Length: 214
Image (cartoon, rainbow, N blue to C red; front, side, top):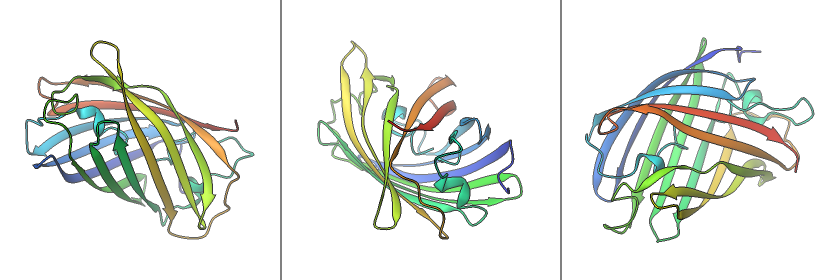
């Protein structure tokens, strides 16, 4: 397989949230068959960001998912050609985000071209006031529809003070070639910011993800 036990990552994200433009670049490494990865992210334009970094972290690759032998792996099968994804995120206070990523590989490295746009966040809400603590561990429901793989998530960000800030995630994953399509399944996610500098101009980000049946 072209997916090696250790794969590097390079990415660039361009976008805008509530009128604030930005660019973030990233480099990292992970273990695709263990579903783990670490990214070092740097804000290259638009620093310091005025909004919660936690709305970005799922946008920074399901190739880094531990897939059981008996569930076809849509993402690893898609390489070396790769795949893209398109995602809508509707937050409970009517902030909404759209993100896309085009994922390719060369040698032992994945490359992501990411677009991220968000709007209509209340200026005094938790996103624009940076009152989120983390992404709560979440389960993504995967299922095939229209010949591609979809993932639906009812997820939540933890807020300072203990409240939950809910978001309906909907992703469409599009392999660039035909692959063996899986039956419906689930992917458990854990996302963690391991470290960051004062304004989050520099962030170290970790994900652990594993596929299973309900």
